[PDB]
Image: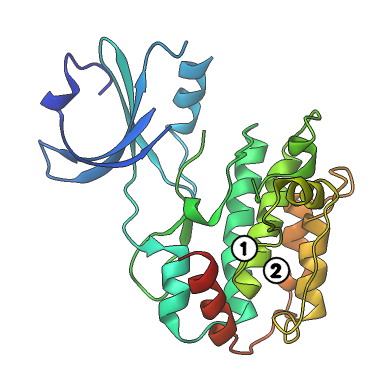
Amino acid sequence: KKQAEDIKKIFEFKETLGTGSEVVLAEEKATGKLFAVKCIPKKALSIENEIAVLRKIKHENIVALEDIYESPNHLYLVMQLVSGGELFDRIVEKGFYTEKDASTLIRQVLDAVYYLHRMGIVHRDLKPENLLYYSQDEESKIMISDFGPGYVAPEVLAQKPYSKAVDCWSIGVIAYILLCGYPPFYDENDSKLFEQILKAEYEFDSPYWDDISDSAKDFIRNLMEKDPNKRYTCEQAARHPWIAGDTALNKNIHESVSAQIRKNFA
């Protein structure tokens, strides 16, 4: 279903879900089914060849590209709507949360980003906001919600040529936040803040990190590594014992993590 004279013949647009192109909550008039439609003005003029590739591939942990419509002046990417809820909301509400839970989340993100990297796509915008649950179910998978300061790799902030390794840094930062509930870099000045990011200066500070395993800390260090050449790839991280083995702990750390999430990501 490529061609439309007017997209409103197809969809009832309801709520804006994000702008940057715009993403709108939409209902297919013929079926009543809901989607997230990314509206892209044609003015932003390779792209059609790439969309044509991903339209045929469904990854368990990535929002699906379900359909594409073309109007006289716009391109519409009809995306799977993810209704399970936000990542942090779930953790705070759960009342019980362990390293195993964080590891399970990261494992899925690694799977998704590995696939994207294999397809030649660098995400460049990995953050907790882009991670959504498929369903309200207890066992719901997590999914990357969309794809094209504190989460950005040093080589990017340094205006250096960068690669897929920048996503791996972002995964490290997300893993850091999942284990303590606050970001690894923060300061009132942007001078030292950027400098701290540029120098990759972070700490597993007490008391927050006292009950976290050495294995988890090692895992994060391999991803939050200043040198993109030394930085773990997604493949390498997925082989780390914290992900692939049994070193993720089973201690309930919900109290501190949720308290920090509420404080820092209110």
Q: Can I make out residue 229 in this image?
A: yes
In the image, what residue occupies the spot 75% across and 58% down? 237
- Side (left or right) of 96 relative to 31: right
Q: According to the image, label 1 marks what residue?
A: 106
Q: Which residue type does callout 2 highlight?
A: Ile
Residue 264: image x %, image y %? 54, 67
Residue 243: quadrant of the picture? bottom right
**Alpha-carbon span between mark 1 and mark 2:** 8 Å
- Side (left or right) of 15 relative to 213: left
Sort mark 2 into few (<14), some (14-19) or many (20+) by Cα contacts within 10 Å. Answer: many
In the image, what residue occupies the spot 37% across and 13% down? 42
Quadrant for the N terminus in the image: top left
In the image, what residue occupies the spot 47% across and 74% down? 91
Q: Secondary structure at mark 2?
A: helix
Q: Which mark is residue 243?
A: 2
Q: Which residue type does callout 1 highlight?
A: Ile
Q: Secondary structure at mark 1?
A: helix
In the image, what residue occupies the spot 70% across and 47% down? 190
Residue 207: quadrant of the picture? bottom right
Residue 163: image x %, image y %? 75, 34
Q: Nearer the viewer, residue 195 or 22?
A: 195
Q: Is residue 29 above or below residue 262?
A: above
Instruction: Residue lying at the far front in this picture: please name it.
Output: 189
Residue 93: quadrant of the picture? bottom left
- Report the number of discs: 2
Q: Can I make out residue 60 in this image?
A: no
- Side (left or right) of 65 relative to 6: right
Assess whether mark 2 and mark 1 are in contact (beta carbons under 8 angstroms). yes
